[PDB]
Image (spheres, grey):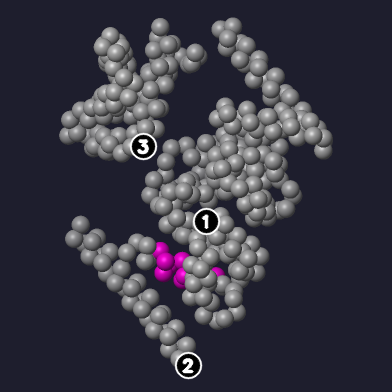
Amino acid sequence: MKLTPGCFLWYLYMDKIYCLLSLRNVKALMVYFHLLDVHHRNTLNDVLFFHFLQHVTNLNKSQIGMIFDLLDWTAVGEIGFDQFYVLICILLAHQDHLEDHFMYRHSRPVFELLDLDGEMNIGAANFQNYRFLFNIKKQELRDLFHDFDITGDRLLNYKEFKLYTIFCTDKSID
Amino acid sequence: LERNLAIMEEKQIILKRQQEEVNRLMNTQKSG
Amino acid sequence: TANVSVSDVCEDFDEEGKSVRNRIRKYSQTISIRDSLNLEPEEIQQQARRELELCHGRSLEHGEDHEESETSLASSTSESLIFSLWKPHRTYWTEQQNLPLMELMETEVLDILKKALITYRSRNHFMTKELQGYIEGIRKRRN
């Protein structure tokens, strides 16, 4: 079974949302998870997750700790293989400029990932955490925050987030 | 009200750009 | 010591159909000539790059795939990675085409794993942490 039916459906969706599907992307991420999971519990302890990011992306350990918390919505103290696979997919060669356009497109939720609270409104702290993950100037983040915050409630709702992403994507394509 | 006017102008400009982009895409599709 | 059948490393794996085996022979001959002439490593890499480009650069009219491949080889990052994939493939064919070590290495790998697993299953001690560190170290160096 193509690494399970759900992964194959995600791969078709990834091919649709990515100009280059690439070769065995899912298998490579699964192999990396297997190497970390010598125990094969199907979950990764914090040390394994932190070390892999340090080994490949050379990320700050404190930044990796924030990333671990966002990925571990279950908060069981371990990272599931799907969460680890999604996190590598989220970076997707983060250094490359082309990835930033794909990162702006995000995924089918397109707002849920930014909204850690899940209240349908994104807090300023959540945006700051995203800025640590994706490099953006603090003044630039404030300017984007003001443009989206027409209400003045300092919260981003889903429809506004979708429109804000669409406007930036259209400008980037232009 | 002034803030309302600005927001509606920005929304109309968004709609204008969307229509322009779709029109250019249709032109490229037909001519290609 | 690839330990991969010759039949796998040279299944004429190149996506364009140019055999791997002919490319290898051309590089082997080029290098033998150049060693006689004492060509510098930078010069050897440049010539080898050009031959890879030409293998893909055979008339580009014979299928679009050759243009996309030559173009990719024309860039510097993808070419370095493409060339560096085919070079060890060519090496593996050459060495396999031409056991106690493999048994030793497999034994060392399993010994390391058993220890890694026992450590993970087992806790706040410096030694355990030091060892976990070395283990991540070895896995990263291996990767």
Dot 2: within a 10 Å radius of its alpha carbon, few (fewer than 14), some, or many (20 or more) residues? few
Q: Which residue is mark 3?
A: C78
Q: Is A44 drawn above or below residue B28 in the view shown? A: above
Q: Position of residue A158 (x, y in %)?
A: 55, 70
Dot 3: within a 10 Å radius of its alpha carbon, few (fewer than 14), some, or many (20 or more) residues? few
* Mark 1 vs mark 2, CA separation in Å: 37 Å
- Image check: C115 left or right of C75? right
User: Does the magenta portion include A30?
Assistant: no
Q: Is A55 drawn above or below residue A138 in the view shown? A: above
Question: What's the chain of the residue with tag 3?
Answer: C
Q: Is C90 drawn above or below residue C119 in the view shown? A: above
Q: Quadrant of the C terminus of chain C?
A: top right
Q: Which residue is mark 1?
A: A134
Q: Is A155 drawn above or below residue C81 in the view shown? A: below
Name which residue lies at 39% across and 45% down.
A20
Name which residue lies at 67% across and 46% down.
A79
Q: Any mark on residue A55, and which?
A: none
In magenta, the rendered stretch is A158-169
- Badges 3 and 1, same chain: no
Name which residue lies at 53% across and 51% down.
A90
Circle 3: element type: helix
Of labels 1 and 2, the one closer to you: 1
Name which residue lies at 50% across and 61% down.
A136
Q: Amino acid at mark 3?
A: Ser
- Badges 2 and 3, same chain: no
Please say whether residue A9 is visible from this viewpoint: no
Question: What's the chain of the residue with tag 2?
Answer: B
Q: Which residue is mark 2?
A: B1
Q: Amino acid at mark 1?
A: Phe
Dot 1: within a 10 Å radius of its alpha carbon, few (fewer than 14), some, or many (20 or more) residues? some
Q: Position of residue A113 (x, y in %)?
A: 58, 59
